[PDB]
Length: 89
Length: 95
RNA sequence: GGGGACUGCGUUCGCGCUUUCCCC
RNA sequence: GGGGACUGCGUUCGCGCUUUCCCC
Image (cartoon, rainbow over all chains, first blue to last red; front, side, top):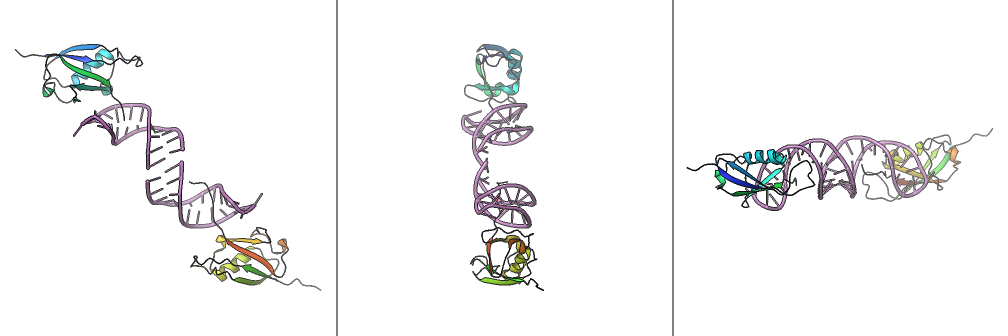
């Protein structure tokens, strides 16, 4: 059986970022476990306008890397990815 | 039939023993120079006597900061004129 | 931004201009 | 030398690099 996993992305609420759609919403994506974490950033960009280089992703306290797979982090159905605006310095 | 002779001037040298390349021992120099000589000639005589280059010398005569291009006559120097010698120190904003 | 040295010059002797540099 | 913004980016989340700059 197995299959793609359903993941949740907690988007921040940042109304001052008027060019992006950061409304504190939860995105639901279903992705293969073999997908790289960068696919999450593609889906988030499509959903919010926020480019991948501006996104910082955290999963159960882990700063997950774009080049690694979802399987590398042992994500299951309902895995919650916390999205933050990446801060320089 | 009068002919204006040279003037005898005295240079009070400072006592600065830390300037080991020069002879600044607090001595008094005596030079005899024509009144038509430029003040710059005094610095030459001082350089010859003390090793101190003309560009490092500051001269003062009766409170006047005399200028190199002017003559001794311009400053009305007479026999026994006392030239005070000091070290020139440059200034300037930090670059 | 600050400290220091140096090349030469101007000065109302307080400083300023300038050259080549070093350090924080 | 120090503090910071900005471009792209890295991070072991303490920070780092980079781009164009600002302030002292």
